[PDB]
Length: 174
Length: 163
Image: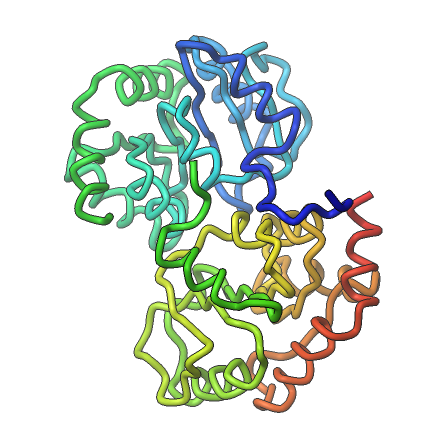
């Protein structure tokens, strides 16, 4: 019973696990665009915040800018997230991601369907293969409206075809 | 509710009282030259810790029996494991936050972007040593690892930053 402890650390930090548990039946959504667009224009952050505020899920958003004016009560901002641990949490319903390789692998591993928002580099191709397999919907960061993002979210969270398609990939992967 | 994939967990537990080291240069090091992979593998093979290396290229000839390659690692789960002794990282912000949160000292190998300044800050705080990916020899990397594992000031300094 030392100060460090001799057991593996808890999956989620203290307040974060309480926030996830408070989602009840609706569950949560993980939102991370990676380090390179954790800061963004006020206009883009409010488009996103407005969409996220309209789903009944709780939302964990990796974000470091100024708090958006339209941030919903269901949404919390985090400078960092234990992404794999959130994706493996039983409450998690969807992953909004830029489509990096580590994130897609964790999404497939844990069977979490995606809203893909590719920005740079391999990310457009990474999401294209997920969209092909029915495990993701794709939206365009620069031009998406709040309703565009909200519809993508509602689709991936509630239409089970996305969950089932990524579970097919999950069951091969492990 | 298990942080590590089964086979990865068995490897981590197999480290006994030596513990493990987590090595990840992130997404932008997809692959590297044979020459660099052998320099790294040679160094990693010479510590008593077991080593989990995020790596997706050709298996290095010099890969030690203490070292395993993974296309993907659960980085926060490994850093939170009681066996973990050090984190060799490119210096991405998320990894550094996790290392600070779990009290794990770092060998920083910054490559691009914010990574040089991220690692420079950790080194200034005594929580990291810094090496150069393109220049480092096997001895350089081995000495850095030995330092941050065996000199406790690095772990103690990063635990200060924790709170």
